[PDB]
Length: 185
Length: 185
Ligand SMILES: [Xe]
Ligand SMILES: [Xe]
Ligand SMILES: [Xe]
Ligand SMILES: [Xe]
Ligand SMILES: [Xe]
Ligand SMILES: [Xe]
Ligand SMILES: [Xe]
Image 1 (cartoon, chains in turn brown, green):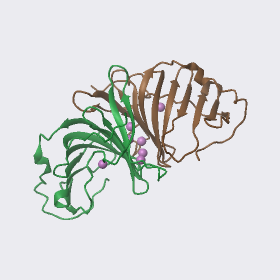
Image 2 (spheres, rainbow over the protein chains, first blue to last red):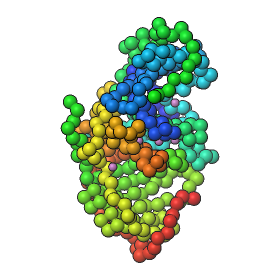
Image 3 (cartoon, rainbow over the protein chains, first blue to last red):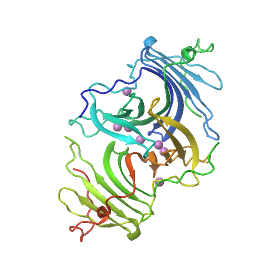
Image 4 (spheres, rainbow over the protein chains, first blue to last red):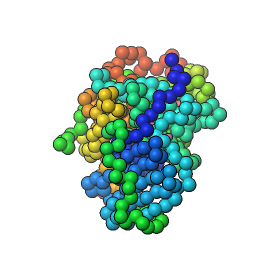
């Protein structure tokens, strides 16, 4: 029985992701503190042994106040910018096309999930697909070929409901500053 | 404790996948019958309501006999071709760099998995990443940015150990034929 609407994804959680940007072939790894109630999300990039990028950023997105802070974790050199952009939660729009349900993982230790997309018969390809657990409606994976081939796959994990540490949305001392554009060296 | 070697993935199973080709933005959906012992894999593309592609193929890959059959499921018009290519199982090479372990899905209904890649500090980006379950070492997802930006993400599910139906590797009557190149209309 094809669901009449998608489950409603959690509004607040702390978890970790891997964002795979195809444009560049890069996997960023991140710890994420997510809050759809306040329309704010904090992403702390993660470092691994013997990677060639010198630079790692914490991002703090505050859509309610239309600004994003971006801190180089090493130098601490902040970067306040504006956000023109409308907030996009990690959930499933109510107009989303159901696609499938299946069990991930082998017999015994497995788990049922669901696949939705923005497929409509008008267009050749989808621009969104998401997989979410059946029980709690947690995000597992999304792909968003947004803006003509700037496509990303995102994987979510170690999710844990709610927010133990709200301090992390408070931008640090060094953030009474300006609008640089930082990227990875 | 960083694993000294990766678990050994199953050699035979019947499951289903979604292959996301970025070049084109297309998700193919498929049923798969996989056998690393005989180095052969049969992929039966799957149809959904109100997609705009008219054409759907069953592929039968027989690496031990260096040939691939390709059947249009509608017209039945076969297409035997040669395979120059070395077989690549769905597993984790023993020289693979461990990356992480984490739980997919929310509290209660979740499942531990593992992430490996072909990262070495010599090269900026990975060209392979795979996620596999911890218990049974089942494939969950891979991304293989092979050959300079011909990158794919693959998701695996409804996997079930072993092969109930070996008939499917036997090419049909209409396959005493030749080497067309078929693609989707
Ligand atoms: Xe979203
Ligand atoms: Xe997509
Ligand atoms: Xe996805
Ligand atoms: Xe991708
Ligand atoms: Xe592989
Ligand atoms: Xe990759
Ligand atoms: Xe992956």
